[PDB]
Length: 215
Ligand SMILES: *[C@@H](C(=O)O)[C@H](O)C(=O)N[C@@H](CC(C)C)C(=O)NCCCCNC(N)=[NH2+]
Image: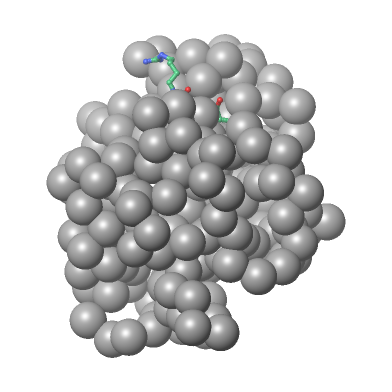
């Protein structure tokens, strides 16, 4: 796997979204991974619908929280997920209104990365593309991050609370990091992204709950 890879430079990443006051991070994390694969497969990069997920995944709890794995299964069984245009994000839970004529993508499963294995996470990013990951984003240092490779010894590998997207990896000024796309808008972090510590003992549980869909 290359020493560094940024899928943004490859055009596998859609612009940063804002989940608003809805706990839909799992939906945005899921959508980002699917958008990455849709690109790999069809050559087109389109915005998929996180709202479709929020309203339709009964195994998850809409704005109350959920898992990316449940989301991928829903897309697989549903046999499709609508585009952002066919199913706009409102940021509130509503009855499932899936429209098959707005179907932009499909899913045939998901693969999970071994718990805590950052080497596996790396191998996966360099081969498949953007991977969905869960981290502990409760620290106020994470909240106010603006630049550099983020790392705070207070981060909790066993307190995963935020779903996010691993969009690449590399090294800054001697510090290896993961390129993480957040869903807290552009005004957050570095234009919506954060460089998180790579190989520093599974920083924030970055490699504890990762997965990606198969098409
Ligand atoms: C994240 C956010 O919107 O900021 C949102 O709280 C969320 O979905 N968080 C996840 C975090 C990781 C997946 C650990 C979460 O808490 N998921 C599990 C919540 C339990 C809900 N129960 C199920 N299975 N529907």
